[PDB]
Image: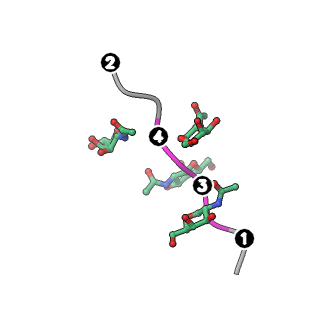
Amino acid sequence: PPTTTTKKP
Ligand SMILES: *[C@H]1O[C@H](CO)[C@H](O)[C@H](O)[C@H]1NC(C)=O
Ligand SMILES: *[C@H]1O[C@H](CO)[C@H](O)[C@H](O)[C@H]1NC(C)=O
Ligand SMILES: *[C@H]1O[C@H](CO)[C@H](O)[C@H](O)[C@H]1NC(C)=O
Ligand SMILES: *[C@H]1O[C@H](CO)[C@H](O)[C@H](O)[C@H]1NC(C)=O
C-alpha cells in the first residue's frame, strides 16, 4: 500500500 518516507533531520 501507499508508503511514506521520512525527511532526514
Ligand atoms: C514508500 O516506501 C516504500 C518502501 O519500499 C517504497 O520505497 C515507496 O516507493 C515509498 N513511497 C514513496 C511515495 O516514497
Ligand atoms: C510516512 O509518513 C506518513 C505520514 O502520515 C506516516 O507518518 C508514516 O508512518 C511515515 N512512514 C515512516 C516509515 O516514517
Ligand atoms: C521521504 O524520502 C523520499 C526519498 O526520495 C522523498 O524525498 C520524500 O519526499 C520524503 N518525504 C518527506 C515527507 O520528506
Ligand atoms: C526519516 O526519519 C525516520 C525516523 O526514524 C528514519 O530515521 C528514516 O531513516 C529517515 N529517512 C531518511 C531518508 O533519513
Q: Is there CB contact under 8 Å for labels 1 and 3?
A: yes
The residue wearing badge 2 is: 9
Residue 3 position by quadrant = bottom right
Categorize mark 4 by other alpha carbons within 10 Å: few (<14), some (14-19), many (20+): few
Q: Is there CB contact under 8 Å for labels 2 and 3?
A: no
Q: Is residue 8 above or below residue 6?
A: above
Residue 4 position by quadrant = bottom right
Categorize mark 3 by other alpha carbons within 10 Å: few (<14), some (14-19), many (20+): few
Q: Is there CB contact under 8 Å for labels 2 and 4?
A: no
Quadrant for the C terminus in the image: top left
Q: Is residue 7 left or right of residue 3?
A: left
Report the amino acid beneath label 3: Thr
First-in-chain label (2 vs 3)? 3
Dot 4 beta carbon under 8 Å from ligand 4: yes
Categorize mark 1 by other alpha carbons within 10 Å: few (<14), some (14-19), many (20+): few
Dot 2 beta carbon under 8 Å from ligand 4: yes
Q: Which residues are magenta?
A: 3-6
Local SS, label 1: loop
The residue wearing badge 4 is: 6
First-in-chain label (2 vs 1)? 1
Task: Give percent across and percent down for residue 1.
Answer: 70, 81
